[PDB]
Every structure is written in C-alpha cells, then in structure tokens.
Length: 317
Length: 317
Image 1 (cartoon, chains in turn green, brown):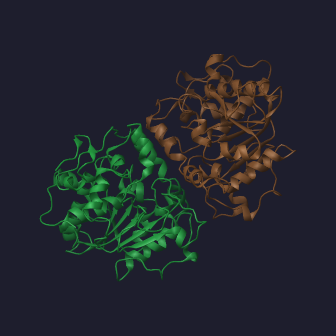
Image 2 (tube, helix red, strand yellow):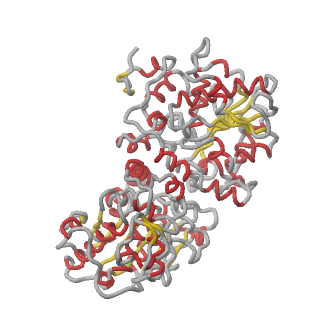
Image 3 (spheres, helix red, strand yellow):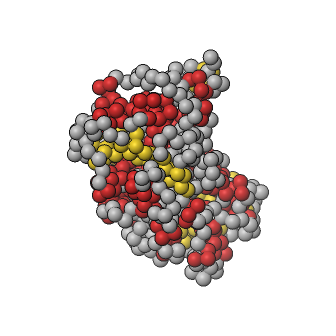
C-alpha cells in the first residue's frame, strides 16, 4: 500500500463538509458515530434510510452518511474525498475515536480507495463492513459503456477500468482495516461474484468473505439490493460492527439467519422501501450525467494504470 | 370486449414485416411455430436466445419473435401492431393454423392489448404463456416518470396510465384465449405482484395464474428476469405449451421444481447469459428515448380511458 502525506482534495473542505450529515448530532460534535457510504445512483438517505440508518441506532450508533453529488455518479475519486473528509471530521468530532464504516455497492470501492491512497485515515477507521462491494468492478457495465451513456463512476466500476486497475496494482485488493464482505452469486449488478474465491469482485485478501450461497447453499437467491438490506445481511452486519476483532464471525450467523427478504426489525413500510431500493437508483442513472470515456485518474493514482484509456487518452507515466 | 373491424395500422404493412423473424424458417413457410414477444428495452434475441429460443427448439417448436424499434421503448400500441401483423403471418404461413405465444414483461401486456383491440387475431392465437406480465403496469416506473426521463412505453407501463386504464375498461383483464401467467412477488420491476390474487398486475380472469411463492413458499426469490429464465419457469412454460386445456396445472410442477437458477437444460454459457438478461435492457433504457408525458391513445382505445392525461391533454368524448 502507498504512503507519505495525504494527496490534496480537489474539492474545498466546506464542499466536502456539506456532503456529511449525522442523525441526531453535528458531525464534529458526536459520539458513537457510524459512517454510511451509499451506492451508485443514491444519496446517503436514499440508500440507507430504509435499512441501516434505523438499524445502526438499534445498536447504539449515531448514524452518519455522505451524499457525494450527483447521486454517486461523479468521479469515484471525488466520491472518496467525501469519505476521507468525513472520517477526518468524525474522528475529532467524536473525541479522536476510531469509527466503523458501513457501505453498499460503490461505497465499498470508495472505502478501499480512500484506505489505499489516503494513509492518514487508516489509523482512524475502526473497521469496514461492505455489502456487495465491487472492488474489481463489474462486467455488467459493458453494454452501458458500449452505448457511451455511462456516468463517470459507472465507467470506473467496469471490470478492467483504469480505476479498478489502479486499485489492484496499488495493493488495494488486500484489506487494510478489518473488513467484512457480504455478497452474492446471484447479484444482477456486480459480476463475477460466483466462484466464492479471490476471483470474486467483492473478495479482499485477509478479510471476512461471505458469499451468501456458501452459508445458505446453491439455491439461495439475493440480488444486489437484498445484499445490503435482507435479514441475513443484518445478522452479518450486527456481528461485524460489535466484534472484538473488527470482522464478522461465523459464530453469529448460519441457515437460521439466512433470510432473503428485508430485515425483521424494519417497519412494514421500511420493508417495502428496501424491497424497492434499486428503483430510485435506476431513475437517477437514466437522468444523471453520461459520457463516452472513463474519467482521468488523479496524479496520486495515475501511475498505477499506465496503458489504460481515459478521457484524455492512454494513461502514461 | 370490443369487436367489428380491426383498427387501421399506423405502421406500414412492410415496416411491420421487418420486425418478424424465425429460427430456420421463412415467415410464410414456418412449421410448429411459437411467437416470442420480448421485454422492455430488448429485442427478441436479447430477451430469449439465452432461454426460450433454445428451450422451444428442444420442445419441438420453431422459435419466432418480433423486435419492434427501438428496443420496445416506442408506443405499446405500435409495439402491438408488430404482433398483430406477426400473428397474421405465422397463421397464414403455417397453413391457416393457430399458434402459441410466449412473452416476457411488456410482451404480455402487448399480447393482451392486441387480443383486446384486434378482433381478427383472436381467431388465430392458440394460447398465451406470459412471464412476469404487467397488465396493470407497475408503480416502480414512478421515479423515472417524475424525472421526465421515461420512454413512451415506460409511461404506458406505469400504474394508472391511460393505456393500462383503457385495457381494464375494454375487458382486457380477462383472458381472451387460454392463458397462463407465471410471476414472482419479489419482482423488482413490476409491482404489485404480492397478494396472489386479482390485484396482481399479472392476473387475468379465467387464466391460469401461477405466483412462484404460492408453491415455493414466502422465501423463494426470483426477480423479473428469473420469472422468465428459471428452471421452475421452464416446467410451467412447458406444461402450458403441452396442455390440451390450453394452460398449465399443478400436476406438472411441485416443490421439487423450486429451482430459481436458470433452466438446467441450458448450456453453461446460456445459463450465464440468462442470469444477466437485465443488463442490456437497462442500458437500452438509459440510452433510449425520453419524454415528459404518456403517448396519446389511438382513437380505437382512447374512449376507454376518459379522464386520463396524455401528451395532447385530458381525454373526453
């Protein structure tokens, strides 16, 4: 993993501050704060208010989240600035206390991206619980890319992208803080997720890698969305957050905990909102920014993807 | 149910012809033909070649399909003109014989729409197998609609649309030929589909209505793609295509056919392709047409949706 000073943000702090919100407190004056990083095509609340915003206070946390505009569709590198600035603001705001990070979809990729390239936060993140993270991107972005209607982050979340290439080559496919990766082979957004090994997009070396079909058998279907919200996903999440290691333990979950439908501690209205998590996201994408090339890598990550083709051309040293 | 003459086509006869194709046979020479009508944001091949085009061949039928431009995102009334000219083709081109019709998503709605408003084809359609059809549309089109980024047919597949309204009021929520409707409650595109009753968007009166949870239990998850692709879906689809009573019944399928994953009879390649059926479709919508209103109903259907607003305004006598 890289080292030295933290690279400069491309955004002002105030712009990064405005993307961070805690439920019940001020970010820089909070206690027991958890950080929530939303998925592609969502704000923090849109991604989590039907699931982990309530469920995290059910465990004694002040829920906090970022909402990088627009709906996580812009550059993932910029999206990461919101996460890095959040953890730096939340550390001091909670009495220099290490804080947990819970993420969905791109939120995971964002987390590991910051952890890899922004060293100062590694000693400030207690742990990482990532639901359906796409550390290797997804091949399923291909058709979107082929029609040149892909958002900045959608380009970057394609398998073989310059961003994912950079993450791998900088050592980012090995966990940097204690990490738990809940995912599924039936995921209709992220693939490959099937082999239940390091071939999988959600797998980080030295981290707790839970593919659902390995704990509930070949028949068990949960999609990309369910991967975050389902009752199964809750027990794994509850485990990871409370543990003494920083990772979820196999003691806390099993076939009894294998419930595909939305979590049980959700009001019947929240169960419907979670069951339809993908619909607003899909709308945001259809309505969001689109371009015909993957965004340029910032100087800190640029040398890790030499040979790849971004908007400015072939990445060179 | 309306009758008299067939409504005059808006599409040229020759234009409609180019939409139809069969695996091996001419439109005029086809033998044991099945007509396949695809989902929203797809072509015939896209929707089916990973699932029912190859399932039909093993069964005995010569697979055929329409692919209305562009990617089923145009007016559903115009999408239907493709199926009407097609049934007149596969009938006359099979030597004056009835032919089955198998459909996914909007495909079902289109079939039932033609059956409702085009008398001539009622005599020519043997049966109808519809997977996750949306005869009452879906509510999940709302966010797209609210952002005015919805294609013509996406407006029309919205719950409460002038089109779904007209369909109910001309007696189109009753099966016009023998009809089977397989669908899921965990369907993330079309809803509501949960009550296991006539409230469900897939339900037709007098039709064989199979909801997957009403046999596999309230923990069986298949999504909008699964509804077409699963092995479960193969058994029910085969049953209906083999029944002398026009439709499937419970004797042909049971708890041992609760297989959510793609059809076992498909090649590993086809089983991977079928699992990712949605990705091209989504990409087609992102790249597809977009407007801020539901398309005007053609004069043959317009009186059955008095009060509703379309692009030209509110409908009146």
